[PDB]
Length: 275
Ligand SMILES: [Ca+2]
Ligand SMILES: [Ca+2]
Ligand code: NA
Image (cartoon, rainbow, N blue to C red; front, top):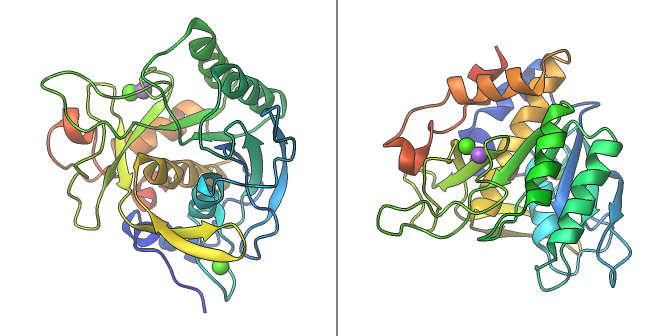
């Protein structure tokens, strides 16, 4: 039987599902450690690998990319879990290797690929403490090209009064996502700062794992795909909205939590965001 992860319900996705909105024809790129395309609960449409030693984007030797992807789009069937936008066209853009790290040149190559291939939404569940003119340029171009770019804020917790949001999440053109629990409390690990935009469920998130498995993971990596999946539902309902309108709708209809430095605008509510 299929189980709906708490997080899907928390952001109110099922309401859209009920209306017949599930992300059909929205192209979402998971820029991460690849997606196990053999998983029975996922449907990968395409993708590319930018990791020199791991040329197949459909082999995930880490498990991270597959987990992120099931949050976005685990199929609606009688098995496993359920994604935020279960009918989306899922693309595996492999930029992290088996050890979960990757070079900036690879990540950037992957963003460039996503622009060229007309992805609607990009999910980046990754981040580093330092930026680069090339990294900024690539996210900026995606957004100028009409792509919704979503990134995990980071897992750096609090540090005095400084921002601990990593890159590319720190860039204004990107939506930086922090993590809450099932009670709406900020996860202690969730990165903080003025660049934080929204929150999403990121503690003990059940999703798909390679080799027809399921398991839980915690991190702002798990929070970001709820937002990416949410932008896919919105576009399925309003195919003519610009990335700008999608973003404003998500930000403008959150459930407000505590201070914006810790919670940004609050927890997204896709039901409200979809109008
Ligand atoms: Ca399923
Ligand atoms: Ca921001
Ligand atoms: Na940002």
